[PDB]
Amino acid sequence: QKPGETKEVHPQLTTFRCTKRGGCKPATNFIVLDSLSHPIHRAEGLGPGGCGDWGNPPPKDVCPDVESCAKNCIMEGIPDYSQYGVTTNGTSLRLQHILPDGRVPSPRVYLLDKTKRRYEMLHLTGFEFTFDVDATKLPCGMNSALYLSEMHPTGAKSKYNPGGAYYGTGYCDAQCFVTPFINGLGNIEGKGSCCNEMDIWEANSRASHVAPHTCNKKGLYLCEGEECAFEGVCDKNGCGWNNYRVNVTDYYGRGEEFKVNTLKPFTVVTQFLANRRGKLEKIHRFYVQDGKVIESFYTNKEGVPYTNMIDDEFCEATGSRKYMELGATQGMGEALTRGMVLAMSIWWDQGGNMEWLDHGEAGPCAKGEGAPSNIVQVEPFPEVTYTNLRWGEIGSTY
Ligand SMILES: *[C@@H]1O[C@H](CO)[C@@H](O)[C@H](O)[C@H]1NC(C)=O
Ligand SMILES: *[C@@H]1O[C@H](CO)[C@@H](O)[C@H](O)[C@H]1NC(C)=O
Image 1: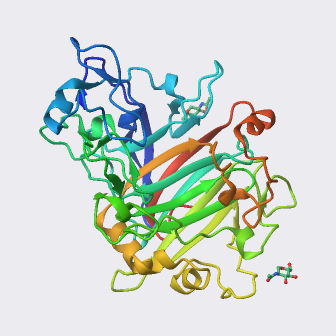
Image 2: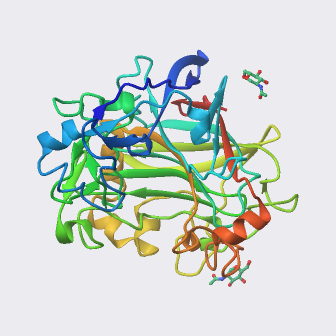
Image 3: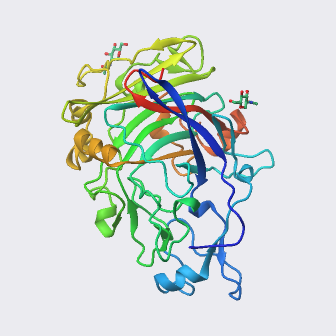
């Protein structure tokens, strides 16, 4: 869309780059909200109204084609991010799903580099990514997410999308959703926005999930028809790793009897182990709490290979068929080597209660517990805090 006049004031966040010799050195980064969460309205002189909702093409009256859409639809800057539940303090990023006044902003943000005009590109194959998290205010049904998507580095800044990464344009993920704007351009044909996605962290205080999702395309791919569906170009399900799905029920949870106790802050480490040729082979998650390393669990389920890391064998044996067909671990690794953008969000799921994350085989949440009206009876103001985001050499971040 065309940037309006209101100024965009991005929250600053200090992050780190670590090496075994130099330790962790500070780096300057900024946060930007998704472009479609910015106020988007019709140009002055046009009647009042918007330029489409999630799930649909933009309106035929103001957006008959890309060029008209680019001048009729205005995206204002956000001068105060705290109104969207996003605040930073030093090296911490706090995301509030629901504000004290009742609004539910459910924010999704991306990490910009120091110039504010390009996303920070992470190249993680062969490296490690680590952060500290406070997940205590996340009951069943909530998803606090921290993940990577293969978005364009400037948000596809172009003639008709002058705002670019500075306004958070260019989102994509493995679900191939239809949004009114794609790469900052009106999505006249109603295509889906698809790209490789690595879900480092999808969790609440009750369950923790990790999942790479491959696509057989590079960068953002605009799908149509069956390309957007289950048998299309992207792996909707991903190759999931959750201690509950592999029958280890005492590893993560609220309370002293769990190895990772979600009643207190803890550190999450994820290593992308590659062979000497640079190809991704395994993904390894382990945690640090109260100065103690808590090693990964090993699977403990009949029919599943004994292993403490995600790999092709584990993925194939657990039925991650689309994952294996659209590239497998090696294809996930190639997207990670090409460069991915870091996204952080907090959300709930009115339609399905986030059951794949923490219910049944995936966790301890009862049927109906994850509904929004029940979440707020347990915690009226769910929120997550991410602190000390840091990446670098294997073994150097913790
Ligand atoms: C704000 O950030 C600084 C720098 O990390 C930290 O020392 C201080 O404790 C933080 N304040 C709060 C309220 O967390
Ligand atoms: C799950 O683990 C328990 C032991 O903790 C074991 O008795 C049971 O057989 C396992 N289930 C499967 C399906 O592997």
